Image (cartoon, rainbow, N blue to C red):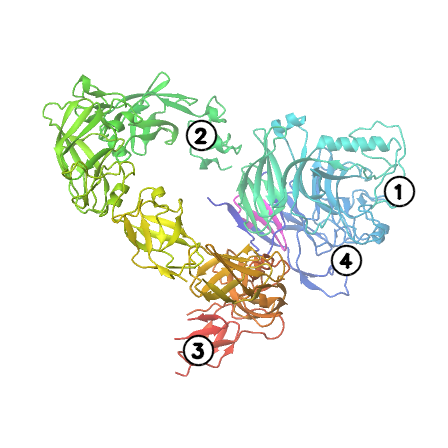
Amino acid sequence: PSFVTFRGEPAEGFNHLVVDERTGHIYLGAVNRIYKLSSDLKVLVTHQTGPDEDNPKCYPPRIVQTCNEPLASTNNVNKMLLIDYKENRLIACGSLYQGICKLLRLEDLFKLGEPFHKKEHYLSGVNESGSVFGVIVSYSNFDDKLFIATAVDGKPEYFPTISSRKLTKNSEADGMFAYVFHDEFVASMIKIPSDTFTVIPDFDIYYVYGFSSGNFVYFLTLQPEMVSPPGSTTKEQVYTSKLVRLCKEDTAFNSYVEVPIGCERNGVEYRLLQAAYLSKAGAVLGRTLGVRPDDDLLFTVFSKGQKRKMKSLDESALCIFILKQINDRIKDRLQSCYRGEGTLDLAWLKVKDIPCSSALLTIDDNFCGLDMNAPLGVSEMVRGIPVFTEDRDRMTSVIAYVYKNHSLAFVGTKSGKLKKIRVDGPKGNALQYETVQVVDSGPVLRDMAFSKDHEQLYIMSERQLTRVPVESCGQYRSCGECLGSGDPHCGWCVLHNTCTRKERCERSREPRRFASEMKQCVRLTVHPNNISVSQYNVLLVLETYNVPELSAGVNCTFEDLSEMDGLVIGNQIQCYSPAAKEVPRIITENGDHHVVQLQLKSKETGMTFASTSFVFYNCSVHNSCLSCVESPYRCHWCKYRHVCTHDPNTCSFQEGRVKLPEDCPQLLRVDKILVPVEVIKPITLKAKNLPQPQSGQRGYECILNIQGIEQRVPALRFNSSSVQCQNTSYSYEGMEINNLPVELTVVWNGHFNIDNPAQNKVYLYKCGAMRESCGLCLKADPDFECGWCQSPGQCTLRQHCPAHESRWLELSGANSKCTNPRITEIIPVTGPREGGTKVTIRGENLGLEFRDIASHVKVAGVECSPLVDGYIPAEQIVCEMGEAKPSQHAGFVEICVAVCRPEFMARSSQLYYFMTLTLADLKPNRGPMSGGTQVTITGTNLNAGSNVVVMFGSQPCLFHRRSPSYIICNTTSSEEVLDMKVTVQVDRARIRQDLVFQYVEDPTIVRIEPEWSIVSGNTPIAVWGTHLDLIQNPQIRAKHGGKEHINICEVLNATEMTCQAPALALGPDHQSDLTERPEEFGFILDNVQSLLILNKTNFTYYPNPVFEATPIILKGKNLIPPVAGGNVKLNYTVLVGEKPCTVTVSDVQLLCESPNKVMARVGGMEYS
């Protein structure tokens, strides 16, 4: 729905709004315009008040007298607007006339009169809108008047800030705006003293809001710094927001009172009035407030602090004042002055403090003021009761009203939104809703009035008036949701089945017709909660509470699917379930069950109000016993029929029924089923509740699912708990894998598969496709029972190999020597003469125990001692060689399993070679103390042996790769000190040499020569620092956004370095024209971490170019960066397949010339 609105008919401007109590017509004050609108916000009539040639400086405006100062067409701002019902007109006071007021006829806006001639006819020079306010009070003839306050602008002689003026019947009459009682000594007006102006130059009173109460008139005002804040001389101005009051009856103006007003929230001060609204509490607020029905209340809005009235702060607070409380404060104050204590204390009015005079008096609320102790101020600032505070978005305006005794408050925001607040201090709670009827971008004005009928609330913006309805409960579909939202306006109109306010619900007054709390809803229950799919048209009884008389008629709707008529008896509703034809359409694909929300559709409303959980459960679909019983519903399984059904009778016979899950037909597991290939073997099985096949039903079979071949073997069911497939042999083709698990399915009567929860499988295992050697077989599991058979030269089970001799060989428990050990290959081919090398020998048929191999290994003559942990039985031996000093140079490796028997020994195919590695030189001789330098150790025979360790200063170096000629390793920190020695140890040999490594102090980065670069980077950067030579490959690092990137540097001297800037190019973020710092910037110099992130750096990144696909003109953004100084600019080159062109570069375009595919390049970037 959209909100009805009136756009600034003059699209040009807007200032004030008011509603006629009887008609509902809305009058809107604006600059140069005054409009009359319908309740709907249609334009009824437009009046042109505007642009008049004038000048603010001139006193009696041009019409009366000639003004020396030049005039200009200026805008006339509607300062004020007030409806004079009695007079049947509208007082629409403008400005730019020296503030002349106009009278517009109520119905047509016909200008009845606009008195210009006399001085009184001029209100104020002030151009500002809303700084003025006032009230029109009327009585029958010979009793009457207008009270108005306005800012002066330092005009003190010309105009009074507050005045009591006359409103004659005739608009033509000269008398208008004359003071009620004018005397040479005292007039019914209050002027600002000249002395006060001189002291504080700018002092001025701005009147925000005003209202008549009882028999007085109140004004909320803003004033300047007068003793607040203290200051010897003029400087800054801060404001103090105060309340003013007058007796309607006091022609003398003696009754004037002025108290400062504000409120504080947790030590935060809210001094400045934005707007206010007088209203009633209604029964709810009044009771807890402790008030009489008639007693009034004043909602207000204040900004934080004393600063900037012109443009206040966002922080704003809605406070409250009970009029009784303010009246008390005033009475309290007066009764005090009458005591004779202290001074009057009103700075702006009376510069010189006059004392209060004591006197005998009955001080009442009626007290109008007396000659002595005349106009007076107030000491104690009156504090208000806080209600709601907005930090993020400043409140601009407020209104409130009584609804069903609950007090609803309306608050405009700077954003153009309205808040609907139930005030519940006296009750208990907070803010119910927020709305943006208005204007999404920018604010709402103080003139915010409810309509006469109080259906809507006209919300005024600078641009437009918007008719915001006071609730939009209709959005809520169900009683549960309606009451769920909580926005206090909403209730569930039971019979209507809709969500709306009390006023909206017909006959809501009657009992249980309207529901306020969730409890009142609606609660529904169905006796047959669960009905089976198979059943049809079942009788259901409905129990509902807290529902209105249904005699209108009701229908039951399971869902959008179906709807059945119902009859009512007692306090119950009787409906029928859907037909089988209807029910399964739903059930299909939901499977196990489908919960459905059965609703009740009322005949009168035609909307579903009440719901319940209704379950549709069909047993037959279940394919297996587990699903049938074990599932969530009541279903019975028939072992024999092998079907699931609701009825017990349908089962084959009594013994066949499965009520419990434990009882179901399933196969129990036994020790793993091992099955050799090509062997005839029976496979016994255990299980539970196996059915006896009934008539027309066949027996049991075992089906093995082997991809190569699926075997069907019939079986015998001995009893309810045991089965056995008959003697058969199984095989799979491939010889690929030893152990193949296979799924097996036990079936009976052809298709019926018995459930296999464990999912037991049969393991088909085959004898050495894999192992040609005796060592390999004995190595394999003892479970296989597979063993080596000497005569065949092959390996199979005893069953498989004939026994000429009493024995076939099986590793009894590893105590089985094997024969014919072989060595395939060994690692470190070469080694040092000194020894210590770790030789890794890999063979096929070795000894099973370590103990036998130990002492077995020899390299030629040299004794080699094997390592226990390293040794993997019969596959591999890790051995450490001893001192090689012998004459041989090269020798074959020998392993004797237990004993060096002739059958039992193995010799290596290739011989182990002895040679002593040496190291001549290191590529970097020097490096930083922190370390992290890539060292290049050059030498000979560096590759030898097993293990390598490099120690600089006895501290370890981190190894990388090894070669015959070279060892590469990364240096550790020389915490010790500059200089150091290099020791390399391979196995037991430790070689040292004269070559030394010299430690040099961590490098530093002083400065970066351009402070900046572009998004794509690759510009030159001249960096300066210290100990730069110490790092071989320095690089620049930068982190922009999520990603981190690096780039290369070239080191000239110890001090100087040239680096190419890193590319930032990121699709998500682009550097702004202004420029941006990276998340991190630094340099990667080995381990020195401090260099990685530079805290101090103010390096900035400027925006790679964007280009879009006869001379050539290429357009795109980001061609030129805003860079400081010089025309440091990018050197662009647009080239064709090979030739560059002459071009003039502009920020937006590139003017290349082609006399006859293109590539554009600047620095590092290329685009095509």
Residue 632, placed above or below residue 1084: above
- The residue wearing badge 4 is 60
865 relative to 932 in the view: left or right: left
Mark toward the start of the polypeptide (1 vs 4): 4
Q: Nearer the viewer, mark 3 or mark 2?
A: 3
Mark toward the start of the polypeptide (1 vs 3): 1
Magenta span includes 1030: no
Residue 871 percent coordinates (x, y) = 37, 46
Element marked by disc 2: helix
User: Label 1 is placed on what type of residue?
Assistant: Asp
Residue 1157 visible from this viewpoint: yes
- The residue wearing badge 1 is 353
Front one among 423 and 210 = 423
User: Label 4 is placed on what type of residue?
Assistant: Pro
1081 relative to 755 in the view: left or right: right
- The residue wearing badge 2 is 480
Few, some or many residues within 10 Å of mark 2 (<14, 14–19, 20+) = many
- The residue wearing badge 3 is 1135
User: Label 3 is placed on what type of residue?
Assistant: Leu
Q: Nearer the viewer, mark 3 or mark 4?
A: 3
The numbered dot on residue 931 is none
User: Label 2 is placed on what type of residue?
Assistant: Gly
Residue 569 percent coordinates (x, y) = 34, 17
